[PDB]
Image 1 (spheres, protein in one colour):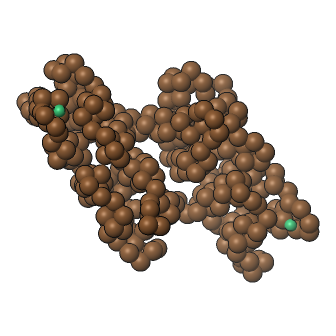
Image 2 (tube, helix red, strand yellow):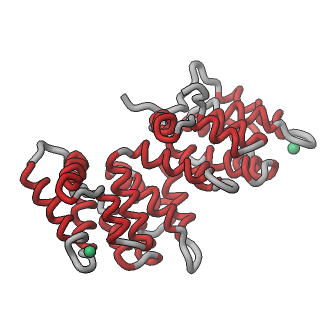
Image 3 (cartoon, protein in one colour):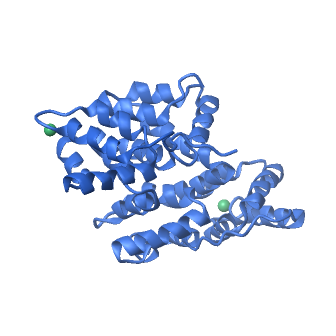
Length: 318
Ligand SMILES: [Ca+2]
Ligand SMILES: [Ca+2]
């Protein structure tokens, strides 16, 4: 299996669903319920058919109009809900790099989080859409071993998943053992090289062997051994490896946790995974935090914003 939460319509009519729109934003005010009930109700390919049928009919661009009547959160939510699938990520990514600064967590997230197949297909979109080389921008903004780890990930050449070579698992585990724990300092290049290049089906075994031998979790060593963004990045990598759904759920669980709430991430993940594996991510919530995501979300958000996320999300019982 491998599930998502948003799917295509049983019997879709874009020309109709389009008219529910001018009716929704017409005159003064706005029916912020009709729209959130119709977009979260439609897949993404569909959202786009709708988007054209709108233009074809009223000679208008829907995102432009929507952006003119929705504000702040929902608005951020509906925009990021209409962004084409294939480009959404590069979009997020592109957003992350600007400024003499940059938003690493976002970078760490998607790159560490996305498969080679994904990363590859991303690098293209980004290029065709922003006229620059993804990798080039990254390095333009990142640094140190953080940078290189990312760059290595960008290469989307993680070894394939074949049969298991215990020797290599033993060889690699040991390797990682001598690199940090048994080294007065660290051999960052070694983690980057094993962590970013080995087939997942492999690394997971290394992870267990590493437990046996040192008596620590590869993550633990990372904490003790490393620091800085380099840390968070190896963490996500290691985590995504074990289970992306998992890594991700933990991402959400932190964006709501404690005082306030992190929307950019809440939306991002929520949206981005909706049609891919959001159902799964949800399963790594009931189990890993004793609470279903639905509730968490429901208690941290409000208004239409909340209403929508809870429709995208779903799963109350769980
Ligand atoms: Ca209006
Ligand atoms: Ca050490």
